[PDB]
């Protein structure tokens, strides 16, 4: 009773929450979509065979930002991007980028802007990335 | 400037056209310039002060009369077209009178190189020329 | 309840309470009458400056927002 | 090729359609989201199309390396800030080495002093003031 | 669709914000018109070929004050001009005018009125010019 024998997801007016969980098995992590980015809708015949490029193309065509932290894929809309400026007292930026490289939380799409061996820099991105980098850079100065 | 028949080939055309009109005695064939046929149509179209656009191509020309013309301009366009069609006929040059409505009546717009029409205080219209 | 309510400039801090109040204000715009709202700006301006202020028409609606104290009477 | 046939869009669904040729997301504010646009647009040089439409409509924009912020012209703020123990030529080399240097809105001031005058978009002013008062506290 | 041969702007009951934004391309800077100066209207056929000379003439016929600070052009009406008087305990007026001339905010239409070697002067102009001059004057005595 089911149609043509290819592979794909047919979307008849879904609402971006029931759509990305269908991609949540080809991506091997669960997907968490925010409330402001769950009001848009999509309709069409889609086909997932490599989803990390499909999410990159749809995040630019629909207008979205996303972050994969190793255990889930958070998805926000572009009007939720926050930024902050934080100054480090007792540790440098390269000794903080080695913590991000060794921990696997480093993201090349939203890097850290600042002088290479100083205390002040500039972050911007999704709120789960900014709330992680601010608190993980403040809690290292109270160690040192 | 469009046909290359010889003298004999014009005489056999006259003798095969005289057989078609039994009332006539002899058909006289004169050759006219193709440039003055489209020159008198533009010299008469500029004298009546009508907006027009000429599209030259091979094997005939065409004139397009666009715009929101008023009442006296569509009286002079018919008085000129029906007096030109009697003289020359519609085999070479053809007029295309189409009238539209003006968008820029109460609107403010910028003309020139980058033209746009502000349809409202919060609305822009960018036309493609 | 945002921890960054406090700004560093006097005009940005007054801008912040406007963009906080905009979700209530466009609700007043959707459900109030057109001309009854439009009557109060002309009535308040001639009180404000004098009769020489020229009247505003319907065409403000696409760009300009009224005050919060000229809406809720006509609402 | 490509393009976009706009029919009465609202400047938030338009600059998102431009956000594929531009390789960054675009964050347009909600005071510059009430103006509307229509017409057949062709995207073959987007960084100059954004520069032309920002001047024809009246807009300000800024690109910090991750996104493109778009405000309306009536939201530009300005400030003057004093550095107690750091020169302007050193802080401007910190901005040159980071990547936040915007040549459209530079820093007006004397070359070896502590006071200058800055003006521009609110995400650029609130970054320069915070990164200047976080460089006087370190010294 | 728009038949006129030349180049120019035609305004039918424009309201001084849509009029100056059309001049904001010949001027290469964005224009910021104030709230009280946007209630006046203008209509007619205009053309821009040297708008820095056209803005000065229309700011006197309509009654306006304008200021260009290197990034934008601010336009206020005439009844918003404000005045100030400030005292400098340890720098001179000729020292402050070298800061304004060297930086690029010095305006020869609204000069600074005061004695050449003192601490007091008198400044008056547009509301974005006065609150900058006052703020830099009270931020150089506290520095020195």
Image (spheres, coloured by chain):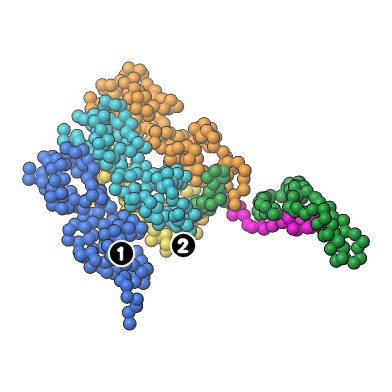
Chain colours: A blue, B green, C yellow, D cyan, E orange
Dot 1 alpha-carbon crowd within 10 angstroms: few under 14, some 14 to 19, many 20 or more: some
Q: Which disc, if any, is residue E136?
A: none
Q: Is residue B123 visible?
A: no
The part of the image, by quadrant, that contains residue D128 is top left
Chain holding disc 2: C
Q: Which residue is at a point 57% across and 45% down the rendered structure image? A: B111
- Residue B100 or residue C64, whichever sits in front: B100
* Quarter containing the N terminus of chain C: bottom left
Task: Name the spot of residue B52 as percent of width and height, x first.
Answer: 68, 50
Q: Is residue D112 left or right of residue D13?
A: left
Which stretch is magenta? B78-105
Q: Is residue C20 left or right of residue E73?
A: left
The part of the image, by quadrant, that contains residue C70 is bottom left
The part of the image, by quadrant, that contains residue E140 is top left
Q: Is residue A96 left or right of residue B17?
A: left
Q: Nearer the viewer, mark 1 or mark 2?
A: 1
Q: Which residue is at a point 39% across and 24% down the rendered structure image? A: E112
Q: Which residue is mark 1?
A: A38
Q: Which residue is at a point 14% across and 40% down the rendered structure image? A: A92
Q: Secondary structure at mark 2?
A: loop
Q: Height in image: D119 above or below B40?
A: above
Q: Height in image: B75 above or below D68?
A: below
Task: Name the spot of residue C10 as percent of width and height, x first.
Answer: 30, 42
């Amino acid at each position: 009773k089911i149609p043509v024998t290819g592979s794909g997801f047919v979307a008849k007016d879904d609402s971006l929450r029931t759509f990305f969980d269908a991609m949540a098995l080809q991506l091997k992590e669960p997907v968490i979509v925010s409330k402001m980015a769950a009001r848009k809708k999509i309709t069409g015949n889609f086909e997932f065979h490599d989803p990390n490029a499909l999410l990159e193309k749809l995040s630019l065509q629909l207008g979205l930002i996303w972050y994969f932290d190793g255990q889930a894929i958070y998805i926000y809309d572009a009007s939720e991007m926050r930024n902050a400026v934080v100054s480090l007292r007792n540790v440098s930026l390269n000794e903080f980028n080695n913590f991000l490289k060794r921990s696997g939380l480093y993201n090349k799409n939203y890097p850290l802007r600042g002088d290479n061996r100083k205390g002040t820099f500039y972050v911007s991105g999704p709120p789960v990335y900014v709330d992680m980098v601010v608190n993980a850079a403040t809690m290292m100065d109270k160690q040192n | 400037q469009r046909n290359t028949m010889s003298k004999k080939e014009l005489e056999v055309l006259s003798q095969k056209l005289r057989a078609l009109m039994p009332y006539a005695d002899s058909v006289n064939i004169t050759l006219m310039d193709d440039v003055t046929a489209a020159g008198q149509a533009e010299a008469g179209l500029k004298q009546q002060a009508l907006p027009y656009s000429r599209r030259n191509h091979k094997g005939g020309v065409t004139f397009v009369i666009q715009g929101a013309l008023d009442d006296v301009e569509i009286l002079r366009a018919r008085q000129f077209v029906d007096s030109y069609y009697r003289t020359w006929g519609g085999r070479y040059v053809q007029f295309a009178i189409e009238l539209k409505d003006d968008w820029l009546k109460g609107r403010s717009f910028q003309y020139g190189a980058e033209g746009y029409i502000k349809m409202s205080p919060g609305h822009w219209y960018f036309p493609s020329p | 309840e945002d921890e960054d309510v406090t700004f560093n400039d006097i005009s940005s801090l007054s801008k912040h309470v406007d963009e906080g109040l905009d979700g209530y204000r466009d609700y007043l715009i959707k459900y109030s009458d057109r001309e009854l709202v439009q009557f109060f700006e002309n009535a308040q301006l001639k009180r404000q400056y004098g009769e020489e202020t020229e009247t505003v028409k319907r065409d403000k609606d696409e760009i300009e927002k009224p005050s919060i104290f000229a809406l809720l009477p006509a609402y």
